[PDB]
Image (cartoon, rainbow, N blue to C red; front, top):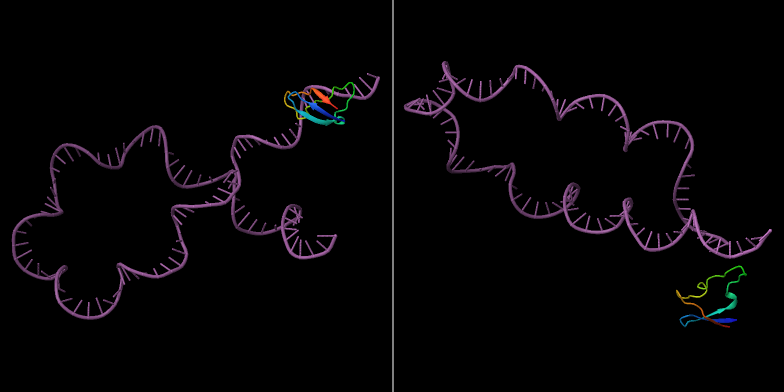
Length: 49
DNA sequence: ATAAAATCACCCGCACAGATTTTTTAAAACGCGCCACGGGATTTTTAAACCGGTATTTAACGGTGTATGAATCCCGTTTTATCTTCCTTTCACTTTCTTTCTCCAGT
């Protein structure tokens, strides 16, 4: 499924779910700045499948 | 995949020309000293100027017949102005090594 990510400054980005990193309960994940060209303090606040 | 054409390192002995490397030698220098020489003040002697006069010796002058000085044309020689260059240098970039930070599976 496609997901639309809305940033803290009004931007919209597109991605597919399986491109997200896979991990277990003990892990903490990976930073999202690698996946999307975000700004210095821009953050994601909404996702729409 | 078939044709055309090219290039370099080392080993083994021996003789000699050229390039460092010690080694010896003659010139230049320094310190100390003494006596050979030149300055200063008398005696002595002689070189040259001056009067003669005479007896030569030179230079200026008038004809002939050359040898050379200035001018021209070249070509090897050396100077000077004018190009390219390799090492020194840093320096921003890139790469590569070393330490650290987590993940994380296992018990």
